[PDB]
Amino acid sequence: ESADLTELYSIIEKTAQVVDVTASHDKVWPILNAFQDVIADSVISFRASTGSSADDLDCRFTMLPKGLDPYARALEHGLTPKTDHPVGSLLKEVHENLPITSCGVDFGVAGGFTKTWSFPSAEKLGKVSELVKLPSIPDAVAANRDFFEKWGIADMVSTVGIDYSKRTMNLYFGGGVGDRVPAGVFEEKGVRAILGELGLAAPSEELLKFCERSFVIYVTLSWDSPKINRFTYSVMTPEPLGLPVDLAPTFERLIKSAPYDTEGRNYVYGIASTPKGEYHKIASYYQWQKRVEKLLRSDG
Ligand SMILES: [Cl-]
Picture 1 (cartoon, rainbow, N blue to C red):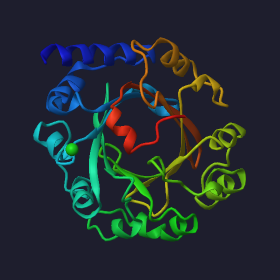
Picture 2 (tube, rainbow, N blue to C red; picture 1 turned 60 degrees about the vertical axis):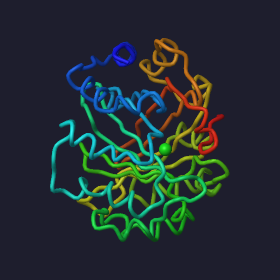
Picture 3 (cartoon, rainbow, N blue to C red; picture 1 turned 90 degrees about the vertical axis):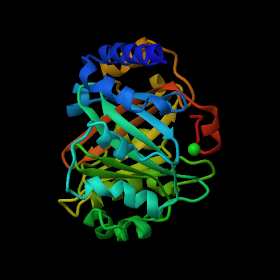
Picture 4 (cartoon, rainbow, N blue to C red; picture 1 turned 135 degrees about the horizontal axis):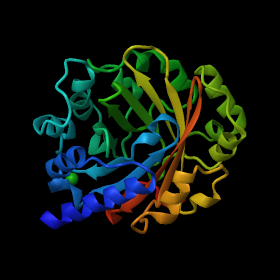
C-alpha cells in the first residue's frame, strides 16, 4: 500500500503541526518504509511533551510481532547508528532471556528512530532478577534491587524500553490485564517516599492528584550512573480534559484538534519526575487493535 504510507505520513505531519513541530520527511519516510510490513497490525499513538521534549512529536508503533527484532531492522535500514556501547546489544539479550511476546518502536518526527520496547505477556511478566544477569544491562538495575523489592515490583516488569539516542533504559510496571502495582505506590505517602529515596523533586499537588488515578509506573536508568534518573506515573483515560492538571496549550490542541478520532486506550498521560522538576507527556491513540484488549488494560 503505497498510499497507506503516504496517508500515514500526512496524519503524522498534521499531528506534529498541531503541537507546533515541523515533521521531517527525511527522518520519517525511511522508517515508515523500513517497518511497512508491521504497521497495519500495530497500535499507533502520537506523544507530545512539555519541557525540553516539546520540540518533537514521538510516533509509537507497538504490539509488533514476536519474531521481529526491531533494532536489527533499524540497523539494517540505516535508521540508527552502529555502536559498541551495550545499549546496542541489550535488546537481543532481553528477547532471549525474558518471556518477550511482542515489541514496539518509537521515533521523533524531527529526531528519527530513538527507542524500542520489548513486551512480556501479562501471563508471564519479566523479573529484575532475570535482567541483572544480562551482559548488557545497566549496573543501575542491580544497584536498585532493594528499591524494586521494597515496593514489591521486582517480579512484575511489564515492558523494557531502550532509548538508543539517550543511552537509557526504562523499566515499566503495571498495565496488563489482571495485574496490579501495589496500592501504596499511588498514595501520597508512597509517592513522597519513592521520590525522596530516588533523590527526585518532591511531588507537586498536581502530581499527587494525578497519581491517584495511575496504575502504571516506570523508572529510567542509564549506564553511566547507579541512580534512577526519573520516575514516571501514567494514567489512561478517554477524558484527558478531566485530569487534575493544568494542561499545556499544545496538549489541549492535540486533544481537540488532532486530524483523527482516538481509539482504544484513547489517551495515556504521564508525569515524569527528575532531580530538577517534573514534565508532562500525553499520547493520543490513532490506531488500536482489538486483539490487544486480551493483554492490556484499556478502559480509563
Ligand atoms: Cl505474533
